[PDB]
Image (cartoon, rainbow, N blue to C red):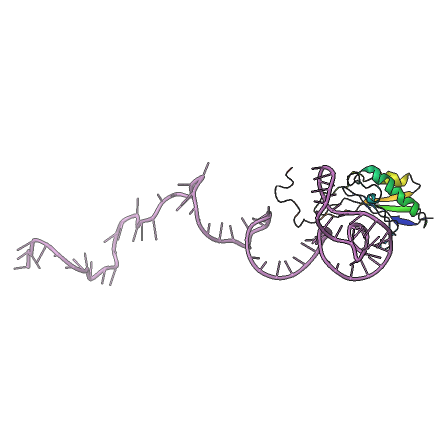
Length: 127
RNA sequence: UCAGAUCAAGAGGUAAUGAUUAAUAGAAGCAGUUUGGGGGCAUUAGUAUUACGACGCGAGAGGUGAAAUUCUUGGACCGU
């Protein structure tokens, strides 16, 4: 008895996208991100928004009944931060405590063989 | 003839018969073995960032000190 989903945690800064799909990813279930729960624009980064809006997906994957699933952490690095934010794996302790069978955890942010040009301009982010 | 001098000697014979070193200077070579993101021209790969095409999804998303500008004629963001 092993049916499998893919969690696709896009653990960005100032949001968190807990968007489980089917195994091929063409078919999405329960689009719930951390933005659709609290609306104050600056606790969307918080691990508590990734706490509740991750196991919020765990009920709606039991509407179709998928016991086991896989994880895909994303950072959101392209020419950018390349490591997951604050509410990154607080959305992983949310899932495994919510009666799930989690084996696969992978960092599927991709990294370039060199970036085009990033924002900021040679002395970037003064103040 | 001596010819003050001055050109060339019967040249085949008698002279140790004549070219210093090779610079922990340089240069050039090599049956030389290589070595280096050195320069040129072709060839070719890598993910990424876009922009679009399909398809699923459903109301958010960018961003920030807090914001707003901005993106959702929902089909965006996200997943592919």
